[PDB]
Amino acid sequence: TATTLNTPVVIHATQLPQ
Amino acid sequence: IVRVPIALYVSLAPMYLENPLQGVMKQHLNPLVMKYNNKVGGVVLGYEGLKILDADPLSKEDTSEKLIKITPDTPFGFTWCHVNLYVW
Amino acid sequence: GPEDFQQHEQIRRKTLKEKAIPKDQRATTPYMTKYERARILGTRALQISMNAPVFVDLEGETDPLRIAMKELAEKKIPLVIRRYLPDGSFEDWSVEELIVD
Amino acid sequence: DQENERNISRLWRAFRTVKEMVKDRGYFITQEEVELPLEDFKAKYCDSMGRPQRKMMSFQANPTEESISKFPDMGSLWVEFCDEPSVGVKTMKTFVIHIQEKNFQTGIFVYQNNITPSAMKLVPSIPPATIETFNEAALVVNITHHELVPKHIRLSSDEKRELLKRYRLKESQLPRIQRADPVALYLGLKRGEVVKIIRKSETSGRYASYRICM
């Protein structure tokens, strides 16, 4: 699988885990 | 259990071109539940506060009509999103 | 890290806002160009052929381009043309906002 | 006077072109001064023997009121007609110290036949004043009177800013006019300042286009 239909293109952390 | 705000770049289906929030949820967020992520650093236990960014910056963030950018060679739309994930 | 991405995102969105031209001062053609009409018809046809919800009533037709032309006649196309100026500035005209021919 | 009359007439035409050049650049010259008849020119700048006394024609020009309003920082202008066929380094030194002591913001120099290459390495060495060198030749005809050559208008700073904001341009992206083509020399154009061209397009009549000097 792993098409651009089930997984986001990029996962970026906006801020530190809070 | 740590709440980790993240920014996504997800695809929107023309089937979901009418409820993009649920479209993004069911395409991307719902699969991520109970599955470890190689980016955040833990198994995602849920999500909340999914907010879709706007492709038109001048649009007030209180509006309910946002713009999604359609792929030039595909009826799918890709947009930035912000969401908080419950990570164990 | 997260803060580096946060500042990268802030710079990107600030540049985007600095490039957008508000609706009150756009100086482009009020009409819809032939290229804009053709691409809006093609994209709407792609979307409807990809099982999108439709607004106009089907008259038994099955050609997605014909359905898109019917929607354009009824001004029911939920699309926006982002006309790009040479320097990267863009004006977001709406399909209904534009006058077809 | 077999050919000395031809020399006098060529010098008079060059002087007329210089007056027109200064006036177009935006200084105060009377229309009677520009359209100077040949007999009056001979009675003014020429002696009884017929020699073209070129020391008399060195004049000083000042901006008009409209020119001052347009360009705030325009200064006086000096024009010279050296007597010797070739301008020497000593004459160039005298000219540059003359410009410095008069505090002229622009000097115009002409040379009858030639200029020594050594007198050219120090003209751009006295900022902010500038020295522009022309010849008695290549000035017997005003190259802006040619129907192929359109009307060139030097765009001010405010108009240039308005142009760049109107087209959302960059100063580099505009069409470019060389610093050494006769029109830029005629207007005394500087690098970075835009000119305006009114073109006589046969499909649209008058047409406004702009070139930048780089």
Image: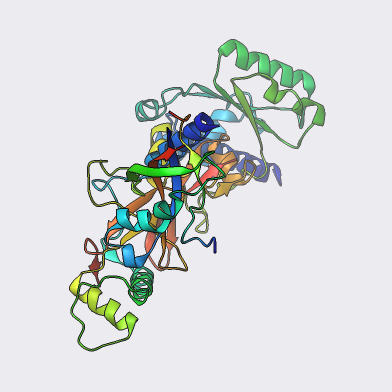
Q: How many marks?
A: 0
Residue B68 vertical placement versus A14 (above, below): below
> What residue is rendered at 54% in x and 60% in y?
A2
> What residue is rendered at 54% in x and 64% in y?
A1
Residue B54 vertical placement versus A17 (above, below): below
Residue B81 vertical placement versus C74 (above, below): above
Q: Quadrant of the C terminus of chain D?
A: top right
Is residue D87 toward the left or the right of residue D16 in the image?
A: right
Q: Position of residue D105 (x, y in %)?
A: 54, 21
Q: Quadrant of the N terminus of chain D?
A: top right
Colouring scheme applied when the structure was drawn: rainbow
Viewer-proximal residue among C68 and D42: C68
Determine the image quadrant of residue C41: bottom left
Q: Would residue C26 be visible to someone looking at this image?
A: yes
Determine the image quadrant of residue D124: top right
Is residue C9 toward the left or the right of residue B64 in the image?
A: right
Viewer-proximal residue among D194 and C78: C78
Viewer-proximal residue among D158 and D37: D158
Determine the image quadrant of residue C94: bottom left
> What residue is rendered at 24% in x and 52% in y?
B65
> What residue is rendered at 39% in x and 46% in y?
B81
Q: Position of residue D198 (x, y in %)?
A: 42, 52
Q: Would residue D155 be visible to someone looking at this image?
A: no
Q: Position of residue D69 (x, y in %)?
A: 35, 27
Q: Position of residue C66 (x, y in %)?
A: 30, 83
Q: Residue furthest top?
A: D101
